[PDB]
Picture (cartoon, rainbow over the protein chains, first blue to last red):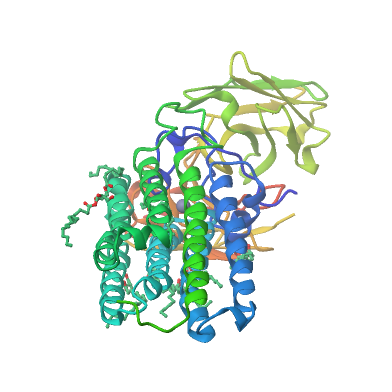
Length: 286
Length: 119
Length: 107
Ligand SMILES: CCCCCCCCCCCCCCCC(=O)OC[C@H](O)COP(=O)(O)OCCN
Ligand SMILES: CCCCCCCC/C=C/CCCCCCCC(=O)OC[C@@H](O)CO
Ligand SMILES: CCCCCCCC/C=C\CCCCCCCC(=O)OC[C@@H](O)CO
Ligand SMILES: CCCCCCCC/C=C\CCCCCCCC(=O)OC[C@@H](O)CO
Ligand SMILES: CCCCCCCC/C=C\CCCCCCCC(=O)OC[C@@H](O)CO
Ligand SMILES: CCCCCCCC/C=C\CCCCCCCC(=O)OC[C@H](O)CO
Ligand SMILES: CCCCCCCC/C=C\CCCCCCCC(=O)O
Ligand SMILES: [Zn+2]
């Protein structure tokens, strides 16, 4: 087609607002202020092809997984209406963050104004996924201790809202602060160490291991840490500049660690609801 | 700095041929597309076509399909344009102009004046 | 083919004044527009590309705007060196096309 013809450009001729990683040298999209050209670039080979397809395939995966969860029979749930709500809040954060991300990566090359707008949606999305992750996971760990459950959901929301407001800062999006963005969102997720230690103290090592929690969360902690470490230090494109332009650069694998980490997270809290269904809502444990 | 230097003015007779050479330097030649622009005296600019040094393909304006032919020599980073069977209508200043992803032209050659005259 | 209609064809203004060169495309060009300035006998130089992005080294008094089929080039506080011809260009559809041009004279 003869409409909106464009070629990939090297990194040195890019405008300022499009230089986010100088280790990717060739294969960038040039600035094109047409959404039509941006959305058809999804089927073109460039630096953002993997970044969009990873979180667009992941967005429909958790969308369909989220609707199957709503139509599962209430036969298997101790409180089907509010159990499907806490899970839906996790699915709400998961879908919004993956949709904000692939949309941002698609319209990244449109203009400076559109780029800054969808970048703030991109950063706010990951906070929503972190807060949404905490809701079904807390409502089960503190099932019989309601007041620790309700303070810990207040502070993760005051932290996630603060993380969303700090993402409205413009120097947040600069490449000089890529280590600052790494620690802010990583400290958001690793803030759960305080509710986890509270849970182990009151329930015990055996309880935490029998129910399977300490195994699934150190998987979560590893995916959290490894994903943030690759992003902040730009491995492997830091080692091979100019050979990871299209496939397997840091941002691409970080996207994969988010889809896998959110699915691993769903697997853990879904186990916590099958374990609750077997012992019921009654509570005389002490 | 990126510079586009093309050949000097040409004085030819009707029916003859010319080849204008645009030599580019200051960048990797295959990375960007080269376009050609015609400007008749006192008139505005007209788009002749675009040429891609990487693939070697070219897209011609329908008006200049039977008039222009784009060639290239990647060893010397030179673009060429052949004009065939020239008439008095082909008296103009011909430019080369380099794209940068999309076909907006940041760099231009100084221009080659082609004068057709049987005098 | 997309037709580009530039207006006015020519105009003359004093130094320090503001001038506006309008331009209309026969079809939607999706902001794939560029403006150029050409001095007497010299080569044209890009002023604004992508409808609004100011090119490197171009003074801030030049500003491009518009969307769809109606675009505009504005020159605030005219300087003596601003005389010459001005052209618009669309690069959304092939064959790419230029406007008729606008001759600017300073008094
Ligand atoms: C499949 C994803 C499921 C997750 C939920 C979110 C889905 C949201 C929908 C995404 C796809 C939407 C369709 C894209 C259509 C699309 O690309 O529209 C762009 C328009 O061409 C805008 O016009 P433009 O070129 O900017 O200029 C016009 C002249 N001023
Ligand atoms: C009792 C208070 C705490 C519990 C209630 C809150 C629960 C969690 C809320 C989640 C919704 C997220 C709202 C996030 C609101 C962000 C507002 C913001 O940053 O605005 C600035 C921009 O408009 C311009 O830069
Ligand atoms: C699906 C259920 C609802 C949850 C999904 C998220 C809801 C909406 C989220 C974010 C709203 C973003 C607002 C962004 C506001 C930007 C304003 C803007 O650009 O307006 C357009 C004008 O500039 C030109 O006309
Ligand atoms: C029966 C009562 C027992 C009381 C003694 C137990 C005290 C626990 C000790 C320290 C609590 C944590 C202190 C702070 C350390 C955790 C936060 C942190 O920096 O995390 C980074 C990484 O470690 C994340 O993996
Ligand atoms: C300019 C300041 C930032 C420079 C870049 C530093 C980037 C380091 C970030 C992530 C890679 C290593 C992450 C894993 C190694 C740090 C230990 C950890 O678990 O920290 C979690 C939190 O306590 C952190 O607040
Ligand atoms: C489960 C359902 C998930 C749904 C997920 C929806 C995500 C997209 C939402 C908002 C994008 C931003 C919309 C506002 C900005 C658009 C207009 C714009 O970019 O304007 C720029 C300027 O006005 C001209 O250059
Ligand atoms: C269940 C949700 C989490 C699943 C694991 C995700 C793996 C990565 C986790 C945290 C990364 C934190 C740092 C993010 C870097 C900044 C991102 C950005 O600015 O685009
Ligand atoms: Zn991303």
